[PDB]
Image (spheres, coloured by chain):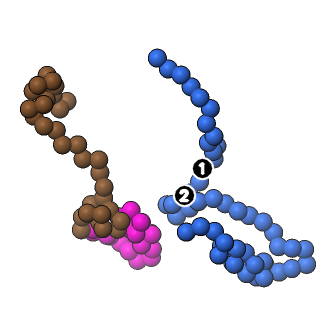
Amino acid sequence: EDLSNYIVSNIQDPLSRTKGVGDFQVFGSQYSMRIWLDPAKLNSYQLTPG
Amino acid sequence: FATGKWEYGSPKLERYNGVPAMEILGEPAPGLSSGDAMAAVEEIVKQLPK
């Protein structure tokens, strides 16, 4: 995951702006601030995901 | 419910090829060429951080 994050952060855009590169397809995405909700605590604190 | 304090920022930010960058321009010494001036600039980047 950190390897894919490094590829799409530091490596992807310079070779994506080089000559002749029409399309790039990466395996694994970048980082993202994933927030996993728990339904029981949402039920306890009278909350929704909305 | 709000306060403030002074900080020290920059008024003009700039990027080159998708990464942050800063711009340095100048002239050669009077009576000198452009190639030896650029060659003299080329070693100063040895003395900068990693």
Q: Is residue A1 above or below residue A36?
A: below
Which quarter of the figure has residue A23? bottom left
- Which amino acid, mark 1? Leu
Chain represented in brown:
A
Where residue B7 appears, as percent x and y from the top left, is 61, 36
Which region of the structure is painted magenta? A8-26
Residue A16 in view here: no
- Which amino acid, mark 2? Pro
Is label 1 in contact with label 2 (beta carbons under 8 Å)? yes
Residue situated in front as seen by the camera: A14 or A23: A14
Which quarter of the figure has residue B47? bottom right
Q: Quadrant of the C terminus of chain B?
A: bottom right
Residue A2 in magenta stretch:
no
Q: Secondary structure at mark 2?
A: strand
Please give the label number shown on residue B23. Answer: none
Q: Which residue is mark 1?
A: B13
From the viewer's perspective, tell me whether residue A26 is left or right of residue A40: right
Chain represented in blue:
B
Q: Which residue is mark 2?
A: B20
Which residue is located at x 40 percent, y 77 percent? A20
Residue situated in front as seen by the camera: B13 or A15: B13
Q: Callout 1 environment at 10 Å: few (<14), some (14 to 19), or many (20+)?
A: few
Which residue is located at x 76 percent, y 82 percent? B35
Where residue A12 appears, as percent x and y from the top left, is 38, 67
User: What chain does mark 2 sit on?
Assistant: B
The CA distance from mark 1 to mark 2 is 8 Å
Where residue A28 appears, as percent x and y from the top left, is 24, 64
User: What chain does mark 1 sit on?
Assistant: B
Which residue is located at x 46 percent, y 17 percent? B1
Residue A20 in magenta stretch:
yes
